[PDB]
Amino acid sequence: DPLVVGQEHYDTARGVQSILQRYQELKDIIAILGMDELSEEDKLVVARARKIQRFLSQPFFVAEVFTGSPGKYVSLKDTIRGFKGIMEGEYDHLPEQAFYMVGSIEEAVEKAKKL
Amino acid sequence: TYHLDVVSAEQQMFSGLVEKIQVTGSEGELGIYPGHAPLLTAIKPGMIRIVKQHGHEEFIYLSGGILEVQPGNVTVLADTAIRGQDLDEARAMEAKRKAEEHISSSHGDVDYAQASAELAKAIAQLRVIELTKK
Amino acid sequence: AGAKDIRSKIASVQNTQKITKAMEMVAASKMRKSQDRMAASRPYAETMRKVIGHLAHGNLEYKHPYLEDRDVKRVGYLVVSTDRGLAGGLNINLFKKLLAEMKTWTDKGVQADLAMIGSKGVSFFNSVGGNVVAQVTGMGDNPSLSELIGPVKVMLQAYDEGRLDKLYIVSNKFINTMSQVPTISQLLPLPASDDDDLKHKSWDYLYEPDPKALLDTLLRRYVESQVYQGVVENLASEQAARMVAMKAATDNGGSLIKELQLVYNKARQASITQELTEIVSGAA
């Protein structure tokens, strides 16, 4: 609640929910028709929702055995900055696989450099 | 020898090597030959005769066109073309019958010029079936 | 879940798959007609562009505005599009490729004037913000040169009044029955890039009376013939893209049917075991 958690956090969390819900609605249209018959705004939300789903992932220190990736601890200010940045499309120029299994947003840009 | 191409938007009408040809024009037909000057040329209703290597002939009626001649490879960009066996003397009589109807049909001078051109076209079809008999 | 609502969705997805198969029938037959029309248009337009290619290079040169390589202040595009959906991304890929070239001119400060031959292009470029200077829509299953002339007549007037300096047509090529590609083609300013007519350099071209009127007429016909072939080829490309899209939609509909049926069967089995368990418990 914004009275306890703040407005910037509250607004970020609702923004994420609104996008990922709309993506769920688009998935049934895409399943029969594919993405080509979507509106161009709908293609924009599909791209951001896929990037958001990838960015929710994180590499735990306790999971270092199953995978090999070093673990990461992310602060709240970093994560709200990352999702706020994706939601307003600052990072629209980066590929999706850049967001997979990274910590803070910065790291994703570096990953994007090496693809 | 040299090659000639003949086309219209609806079809390629002819293409191939020609020892010679004879072609309608503006101030009447002309003969054309390998050595002929590179004369870019307008066309009024008439025919073209297609004499291929070793002297073998075809006989094409044209509604109209343009005969560009930069090269020895020449082209006629015809507005509409029918050959003297793709038409027949009864089809040329049907063209003449349409011309006689068009002459009857209206008073307007440009209409009358269209009807007169349709007559010239119909007689050119008859003439091409005569050339086809020759 | 829910047995009746799932069985209703299964019925609807079944009938939709059956329709997409029939649409794939209409799309293939129209492809047959469209490609044989193209095959007829190809010889005339190909030889007309050859003819002008010979006029490009060879002496006794008259001087004419479509012939010289003047400087570029603004650029014209003739854009063909569909008016329909269900053609996959054919229009999107063409529009993106144009947008890339128009961006490259906008980097140079060279403006773009756009003439649209289809409704999808009008909608996209008006809502994106390209300067649509001409537009015709809904040409029909058999397109005819006559209707297409007006937009071209406008683009011609923009060139010959001197405003418009370079002109292109953008269209999809029917490379194969199942492969096509979007292309931007240089159109009216006759590219001197083309081969010199050194192969028959004996000839310096000569004229019947008034080379200006004759040559003007001939170039008018050249530009038009190029636009008509580019449209007929884009319609053949459209029918191929629609048949591929409908085939994909048929396979995806079958894929849903095979999974909804598993949800339904699991639900009927659970319903059958929740009851009976409750009738034996009640019988006590």
Image (tube, grey):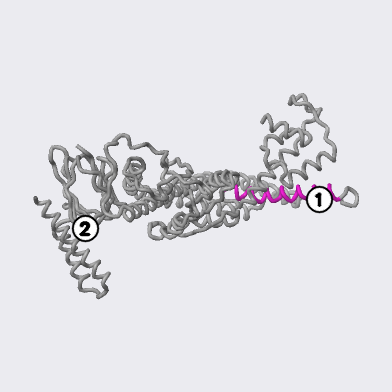
Using the image as rendered, state which of residue C173 and residue B37 is in the foreground: B37
Q: Is residue C201 above or below residue B46?
A: above
Which stretch did the figure color magenta?
A: A7-32
Q: Is residue B86 above or below residue B115?
A: above
Q: In the rendered image, which quarter is residue B112 located in? A: bottom left
Horizontal placement of C182 versus A59: left or right?
A: left
Q: Position of residue C250 (x, y in %)?
A: 51, 47
* Residue tagged 2: B45
The answer for which chain carries disc 1 is: A
Q: Residue at x 53, y 46 (%)?
A: C98
| Identity of the residue furthest to the right in this view | A4
Q: Position of residue C180 (x, y in %)?
A: 46, 42
Q: For the residue marked with disc 2, what is the amino acid?
A: Pro
Dot 1 falls on a residue whose secondary structure is helix
Q: In the rendered image, which quarter is residue C143 located in? A: bottom left
| Identity of the residue furthest to the bottom in this view | B107
| Residue C46 in sight from this viewpoint | no
Q: For the residues labelled 1 and 2, say whether their Cβ atoms are less than 8 Å apart.
A: no
